[PDB]
Image: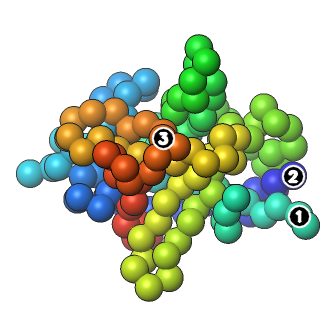
Amino acid sequence: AFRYTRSQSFDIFDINQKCFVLESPTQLVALHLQSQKVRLNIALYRPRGTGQMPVALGIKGYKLYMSCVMSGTEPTLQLEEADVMRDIDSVELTRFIFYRLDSPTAGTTRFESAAFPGWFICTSLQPRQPVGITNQPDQVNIATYKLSG
Protein backbone atom coordinates (compact mmCIF):
# COMPACT_ATOMS: atom_id res chain seq x y z
CA ALA A 1 0.00 0.00 0.00
CA PHE A 2 2.79 2.55 0.87
CA ARG A 3 6.42 2.83 -0.15
CA TYR A 4 9.10 5.02 1.51
CA THR A 5 10.34 7.79 -0.76
CA ARG A 6 12.40 10.02 1.59
CA SER A 7 12.68 11.68 5.00
CA GLN A 8 12.92 15.35 5.87
CA SER A 9 13.34 17.28 9.11
CA PHE A 10 10.83 19.88 10.17
CA ASP A 11 10.34 22.38 12.93
CA ILE A 12 6.80 22.43 14.29
CA PHE A 13 4.58 24.60 16.50
CA ASP A 14 0.83 24.33 17.08
CA ILE A 15 -1.47 27.25 16.25
CA ASN A 16 -1.05 28.66 19.76
CA GLN A 17 2.78 28.61 19.49
CA LYS A 18 3.25 25.51 21.65
CA CYS A 19 6.10 23.32 20.49
CA PHE A 20 6.75 19.65 21.24
CA VAL A 21 9.16 18.42 23.91
CA LEU A 22 10.08 14.80 24.69
CA GLU A 23 9.85 14.23 28.43
CA SER A 24 10.47 10.49 28.30
CA PRO A 25 10.38 7.78 25.62
CA THR A 26 6.67 7.49 26.39
CA GLN A 27 5.65 11.18 26.82
CA LEU A 28 5.68 13.95 24.26
CA VAL A 29 4.20 17.23 25.49
CA ALA A 30 3.26 20.51 23.92
CA LEU A 31 4.34 23.67 25.70
CA HIS A 32 5.40 27.26 25.34
CA LEU A 33 9.18 27.50 25.49
CA GLN A 34 9.80 30.89 27.16
CA SER A 35 14.28 22.78 27.51
CA GLN A 36 14.44 20.73 24.31
CA LYS A 37 12.24 21.57 21.31
CA VAL A 38 11.57 18.50 19.14
CA ARG A 39 11.93 18.49 15.38
CA LEU A 40 10.01 15.94 13.36
CA ASN A 41 11.72 13.66 10.93
CA ILE A 42 8.83 13.18 8.56
CA ALA A 43 9.14 10.13 6.31
CA LEU A 44 7.02 10.60 3.26
CA TYR A 45 5.44 7.77 1.36
CA ARG A 46 3.75 7.10 -1.99
CA PRO A 47 0.59 4.97 -2.28
CA ARG A 48 -0.77 3.47 -5.44
CA GLY A 49 -4.12 4.10 -7.16
CA THR A 50 -8.77 10.40 3.72
CA GLY A 51 -5.81 12.67 2.77
CA GLN A 52 -3.12 13.96 0.41
CA MET A 53 0.38 13.04 1.64
CA PRO A 54 1.03 9.84 3.65
CA VAL A 55 3.85 10.27 6.18
CA ALA A 56 5.42 8.65 9.24
CA LEU A 57 6.32 11.06 12.08
CA GLY A 58 9.70 10.54 13.74
CA ILE A 59 10.84 12.37 16.86
CA LYS A 60 14.12 13.54 15.51
CA GLY A 61 17.19 12.31 17.35
CA TYR A 62 15.24 9.80 19.44
CA LYS A 63 14.44 6.97 16.96
CA LEU A 64 10.80 7.05 17.96
CA TYR A 65 7.76 7.21 15.68
CA MET A 66 4.16 8.26 16.33
CA SER A 67 1.57 5.52 15.96
CA CYS A 68 -2.17 5.30 16.58
CA VAL A 69 -3.37 2.15 18.25
CA MET A 70 -6.38 0.85 20.12
CA SER A 71 -5.79 0.91 23.85
CA GLY A 72 -8.61 -0.64 25.80
CA THR A 73 -11.51 0.23 23.59
CA GLU A 74 -10.21 3.70 22.58
CA PRO A 75 -7.80 5.02 19.96
CA THR A 76 -4.54 6.23 21.50
CA LEU A 77 -1.49 8.07 20.21
CA GLN A 78 1.75 6.53 21.19
CA LEU A 79 5.47 6.49 20.55
CA GLU A 80 7.13 3.26 19.44
CA GLU A 81 10.85 2.51 19.11
CA ALA A 82 10.02 1.29 15.66
CA ASP A 83 12.28 0.81 12.65
CA VAL A 84 12.03 2.93 9.52
CA MET A 85 9.60 0.92 7.44
CA ARG A 86 10.42 0.79 3.69
CA ASP A 87 7.11 -0.92 2.90
CA ILE A 88 3.85 -0.34 4.73
CA ASP A 89 2.00 -3.34 3.32
CA SER A 90 -0.16 -4.43 6.26
CA VAL A 91 -3.00 -3.04 8.32
CA GLU A 92 -0.74 -3.47 11.37
CA LEU A 93 1.95 -1.12 9.95
CA THR A 94 -0.57 1.49 8.91
CA ARG A 95 -0.62 2.53 12.57
CA PHE A 96 2.48 4.69 11.76
CA ILE A 97 0.93 6.39 8.75
CA PHE A 98 -0.61 9.87 8.97
CA TYR A 99 -2.04 11.98 6.19
CA ARG A 100 -0.38 15.36 6.20
CA LEU A 101 -3.08 17.83 5.24
CA ASP A 102 -1.79 21.24 4.15
CA SER A 103 -3.86 24.39 3.71
CA PRO A 104 -2.49 26.18 0.66
CA THR A 105 -3.36 29.78 1.65
CA ALA A 106 -2.66 29.56 5.36
CA GLY A 107 0.31 27.15 5.31
CA THR A 108 -1.10 25.31 8.30
CA THR A 109 -1.17 21.56 8.55
CA ARG A 110 -3.18 18.82 10.19
CA PHE A 111 -2.23 15.15 10.60
CA GLU A 112 -4.98 12.51 10.18
CA SER A 113 -4.38 8.88 11.21
CA ALA A 114 -4.53 6.41 8.32
CA ALA A 115 -5.26 3.56 10.75
CA PHE A 116 -8.00 5.65 12.46
CA PRO A 117 -9.62 7.80 9.77
CA GLY A 118 -11.38 10.85 11.26
CA TRP A 119 -8.72 10.96 14.04
CA PHE A 120 -6.24 13.87 14.26
CA ILE A 121 -3.01 14.60 16.15
CA CYS A 122 -3.91 17.22 18.73
CA THR A 123 -2.66 19.24 21.67
CA SER A 124 -4.44 20.43 24.77
CA LEU A 125 -5.49 24.07 25.10
CA GLN A 126 -3.46 23.83 28.29
CA PRO A 127 0.34 23.63 28.05
CA ARG A 128 2.50 20.85 29.50
CA GLN A 129 -0.02 18.13 28.58
CA PRO A 130 0.77 15.14 26.40
CA VAL A 131 0.02 15.27 22.69
CA GLY A 132 -2.97 13.06 21.76
CA ILE A 133 -5.52 12.16 19.08
CA THR A 134 -9.13 13.26 18.68
CA ASN A 135 -12.09 12.81 16.36
CA GLN A 136 -13.15 16.41 17.18
CA PRO A 137 -10.07 18.26 15.86
CA ASP A 138 -9.74 21.94 16.89
CA GLN A 139 -12.77 21.49 19.22
CA VAL A 140 -11.52 22.18 22.75
CA ASN A 141 -8.01 21.17 21.57
CA ILE A 142 -5.64 22.23 18.80
CA ALA A 143 -5.17 19.98 15.77
CA THR A 144 -3.55 22.69 13.63
CA TYR A 145 0.21 23.19 13.19
CA LYS A 146 2.80 25.24 11.38
CA LEU A 147 5.75 23.35 9.84
CA SER A 148 9.03 24.66 8.44
CA GLY A 149 11.82 22.44 7.03
Q: Position of residue 61 (x, y in %)?
A: 44, 43
Q: Indicate the position of residue 13 as horizontal and vertical percent values.
A: 31, 58
The residue under the point 61% across, 18% down is 73
Label 3: state its secondary structure. Answer: strand
Residue under pointer 2: 1
What whole-number distance in Å separates the C-alpha atoms at marks 2 and 3? 25 Å
Q: Which residue extends farthest bottom? A: 105
- Please indicate whether residue 147 sits to the left or right of residue 135 in the image: left
1 and 2 marks in contact (CB < 8 Å): yes
Residue 45 image point, x, y percent? 73, 60
Front position in the image: 5 or 70? 70
Q: Is residue 113 above or below residue 27?
A: below
Camera sees residue 38? no
Q: Are marks 1 and 3 in contact (CB under 8 Å)?
A: no
Spatial CA span between label 1 and label 3: 27 Å
- Say what amino acid the circle numbered 2 marks: Ala
Q: Nearer the viewer, residue 77 or 79?
A: 77
Q: Which mark is residue 142?
A: none
CB within 8 Å, label 2 to label 3: no
Residue type marked 3: Thr
Q: Which residue is mark 1?
A: 48
Q: Residue 25 lies in what quarter of the image?
A: top left
Q: Residue furthest right?
A: 49
Tell me which colouring the rendered structure shows: rainbow
Establish if 88 lies above or below 46.
Answer: above
Neighbours of disc 1 within 10 Å: few (<14), some (14-19), many (20+): few
Residue that mark 3 sits on: 134
Give the mark toward the camera: 2 or 3. Answer: 3
Residue drawn 40% across and 80% down?
106
